[PDB]
Structures are given as structure tokens and as C-alpha cells.
Image (cartoon, helix red, strand yellow):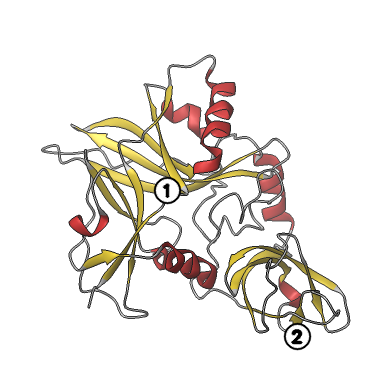
């Protein structure tokens, strides 16, 4: 009966990045350009713009996946909101401190607003039930910048369904199940800090990287990989076709073909779905992971429909 499902993302938190130098400061640490809302004309309606990016380490590997919210109030830039994994709020705050030393910028946690995801309950069908972009103080409702398949982001001090018409509370299992089925990585389990490579994490397919931009931490290796050739290994949505063990699948379990050749590695999942870093060329033929006897468990790799 409900058109939208509202998920409170406890695994996600916000940081407020303000000051007159918040933009050049964040630009040198992120993979993308900043979501700067268009300059307000004639009057002053409060606006918000969303962007996706990763904070990389010096060796060009993903540290944190972040959703950026460019804030505008009274025709002027209000600052920025950084949405990161709850478990790496501190590490990110320390990483930002390590580079803020010489500039006019303030980084502080923003517990005032909570992270929510708004997904359309109707699969394939569009609206309506149409949703309108909301901004300013108390609440922000904006399209997920990664893909339309990820619905909307709701930043609010209140409850999700209270603002969303035809919205109902969602079971957090269904949100993570939706991400794994769509091949959407999010968080430290899907993107291990200092292990996951951004382009292999599908950062370009998710509007998270700019190649027409100035210098940033890990730019050199990123640019090189993007230009030298086709990304040979990618995170792909996987689904298990055989019963899983009591413990589950080990976070780095080898993906094998019928002959025993290592074609990939299980990353993370939930239930019978997840992501695996696989050699794109070897995703058709029958795949499996070792369990107890030596042959079980069977796995199926898929190509997300929202990818180019």
C-alpha cells in the first residue's frame, strides 16, 4: 500500500565542514568535484546539491566512501555535510585534521540530522507517489548521487515517513539486500579502508570521480589506471545458489571456476547476496567458493542494469 520505504541508516553519520576555505580544502582530499548548488537569483530559496566521492590514501586506495551535500542559505554557501560510515567518523576527522592545519575550516560531527534512505517500494514502476527535492534547516531530501536505483537520501532530525507521503518504515535488512542485489557498495565491509581500489569499486559508474579536476590525494594512480586500459577487476553483485554455512562466507573467500582457477574474491554481503571482486572476463562460466567437502557453495555473478 505504501509507495516509499524509509530506512534509518545507523551505519551512516554526518560531519559538518564549514568556513571560507571548506571548498579548496575538501577538493584536495576527494576524488570528485564538490556538489556546489547553482547561485541563487532574484530571491533566496534554500538549496542543496548531492555528490559522491571517495577519500583515498597516498597509494591510490579507497579509505572512505562519502556522500557530499553542498549547502546554500540566503544566496550564500552555508558549508558542507559529509556522510560517511559510522565506524570511521573518528579516523576521517583525524584524516581531515592532518590536512586542515594551514586553512580556515571547521570539521565537527552533525548529530542534529540523521541519515535515512528513501526507496520506491514499486520495482521497475516509477512513482507517483512523486517526490520533490527538499532543502534547508531541519530536513534535506535529495536524489542519491550514485544512481537512481539508490532512490533518495533523507537528512532529518524527525522520522522518515512523517515527511515522505505514502512512506512507511523499512526493515534495514531490505535496504542492504537492495544494495547487494543492485551491486551498490557502501561502507567499510564493502570497501575495506586501504585495500579496495576506487575504479575497481566502480567509482566512475557511480559519479564519484573527476578527471577534469585539480590535484587530490591518490589522483596520479587513479588517472593512470582509468587511461591505461579497461578495469579488469570489478565489484559485481553475487547470489549464492547453494545453502550457506552457520558462520557464513569468510570476508575474503576465493571465487573459483569449475577447474579451481581463482577468478575473484568475496567482499561482503548479507544473507544469500553480496559483492565479489571478480575478473570481468571470467563472470559467465559456473562459479563457486570452498566450504567443507571441497566443491560447495555455488555462486552466480550479475551485471547491474544501471551501469554503462
Q: Residue lying farthest top?
A: 102
> Which label belongs to residue 259?
none
Q: Position of residue 274 (x, y in %)?
A: 60, 68
* Helix, strand or loop under label 2: loop
Q: Are marks 2 and 1 in contact (CB under 8 Å)?
A: no
Q: Where is residue 164 in the image (x, y as percent from the top left)?
A: 21, 60
206 vs 150, left or right, is: right
Quadrant of the image containing the N terminus: bottom left
The residue that appears at 41% across and 52% down in the rendered structure is 9
Regarding residue 307, the answer to whether it shows in the image is: no
173 vs 216, left or right, is: left
Quadrant of the image containing the C terminus: bottom right
Q: Mark 2 points at which residue?
A: 286
Q: How many marks?
A: 2
Q: In this view, does 140 lie above or below 75?
A: below
Q: Which of marks 2 and 1 is nearer the N terminus?
A: 1
Q: Position of residue 54 (x, y in %)?
A: 56, 45
Q: Quick one: label 2, few (<14), some, or many (20+) residues within 10 Å? A: some
Q: Position of residue 259 (x, y in %)?
A: 88, 82
Dot in front, 2 or 1: 2
* Structural distance between the alpha carbons of marks 2 and 1: 37 Å
* Helix, strand or loop under label 1: strand
Closer to us: 192 or 297: 297
Q: Name the residue under label 1.
A: 51
* Displayed quadrant of residue 201: bottom right
Regarding residue 95, the answer to whether it shows in the image is: yes
The residue that appears at 68% across and 84% down in the rendered structure is 242
Q: In this view, does 162 lie above or below 287?
A: above
Q: Residue lying farthest left?
A: 43
Q: Residue lying farthest front?
A: 246
Q: Quick one: label 1, few (<14), some, or many (20+) residues within 10 Å? A: many
Amino acid at each position: 500500500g505504501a509507495a516509499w520505504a524509509c530506512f534509518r541508516l545507523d551505519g551512516r553519520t554526518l560531519l559538518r565542514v564549514r568556513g571560507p576555505d571548506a571548498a579548496p580544502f575538501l577538493l584536495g582530499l576527494l576524488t570528485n568535484e564538490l556538489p556546489l548548488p547553482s547561485p541563487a537569483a532574484a530571491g533566496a530559496p534554500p538549496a542543496a546539491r548531492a555528490g559522491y566521492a571517495h577519500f583515498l590514501n597516498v597509494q591510490g586506495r579507497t579509505l572512505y566512501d562519502v556522500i557530499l551535500y553542498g549547502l546554500q542559505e540566503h544566496s550564500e554557501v552555508s558549508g558542507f555535510l559529509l556522510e560517511c560510515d559510522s565506524s570511521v567518523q573518528g579516523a576521517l576527522q583525524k584524516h581531515l585534521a592532518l590536512y586542515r592545519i594551514r586553512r580556515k575550516v571547521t570539521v565537527e560531527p552533525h548529530p542534529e540530522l540523521r541519515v535515512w534512505a528513501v526507496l520506491p517500494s514499486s520495482p521497475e514502476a516509477c512513482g507517483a507517489a512523486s517526490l520533490q527535492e527538499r532543502a534547508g534547516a531541519a530536513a534535506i531530501l535529495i536524489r542519491d548521487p550514485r544512481t537512481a536505483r539508490m532512490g533518495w537520501r533523507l537528512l532529518t532530525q524527525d522520522e522518515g515517513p512523517a515527511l515522505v507521503p505514502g512512506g512507511r518504515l523499512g526493515d534495514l535488512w531490505d535496504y542492504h539486500q537492495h544494495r547487494y542485489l543492485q551491486g551498490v557498495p557502501e561502507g567499510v565491509r564493502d570497501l575495506p579502508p586501504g585495500v579496495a581500489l576506487p575504479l575497481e569499486s566502480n567509482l566512475a559508474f557511480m559519479n564519484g570521480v573527476s578527471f577534469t579536476k585539480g590535484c587530490y590525494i591518490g589522483q596520479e594512480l587513479t588517472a593512470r589506471t582509468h587511461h591505461m586500459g579497461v578495469i579488469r577487476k570489478r565489484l559485481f553483485p553475487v547470489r549464492f545458489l547453494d545453502p550457506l554455512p552457520t558462520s557464513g562466507i569468510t570476508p575474503g573467500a576465493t571465487v573459483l571456476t569449475a577447474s579451481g582457477q581463482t577468478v575473484g574474491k568475496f567482499r561482503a554481503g548479507q544473507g544469500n547476496v553480496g559483492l565479489a571482486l571478480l575478473w570481468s572476463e571470467k563472470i559467465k562460466g559456473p562459479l563457486h567458493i570452498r566450504a567443507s567437502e571441497g566443491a560447495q557453495v555455488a555462486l552466480a555473478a550479475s551485471v547491474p542494469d544501471w551501469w554503462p
